[PDB]
Length: 128
Ligand SMILES: [Cu+2]
Ligand SMILES: [Cu+2]
Image (tube, rainbow, N blue to C red; front, side, top):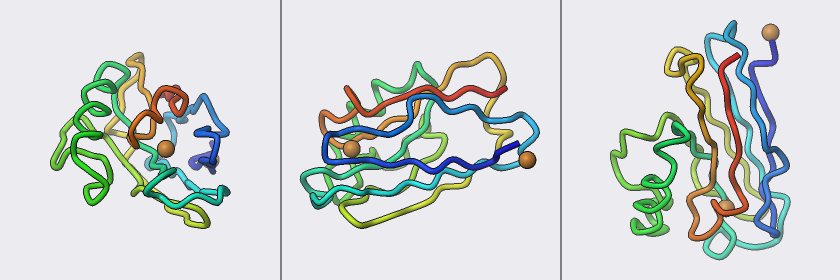
C-alpha cells in the first residue's frame, strides 16, 4: 500500500502525525522526517524513533541521558527498531526499515527522544 510516510517536527514540539499504519504487504517501510521550524537541533531537535509501545519509556529515559552528540539515543539500544537522526530547522532525514522486524497485534510507538519532547511528540504505529 503506501510504504512511506512523510512526517514533520516543528517548533511547538509537534509531529503532524499521531498514527502510522504499516501495510503487512510492504517489504520495507520508509519515514521521511522534516523540520519546518526555525530552531536548531540543540534546542528543538527532532528524531523519529520506533520501539514497542512498552519499550518507549526506557528508550526515552536513557536517550535523554546520552546527550546531543549521541542523538539522545543510548548507544547500541536494542529496543530501537528504527530511527532517523536528530534534525534541526531546515533539515531532513529518512529511515527505511524491514517490515519483518514488526509483528501483528503488538502495539508500537514512534517518538522523539530530545529531552521532554516525547510527552507531546509521540504516536502510534501498527502492522495491519
Ligand atoms: Cu503499495
Ligand atoms: Cu523533538
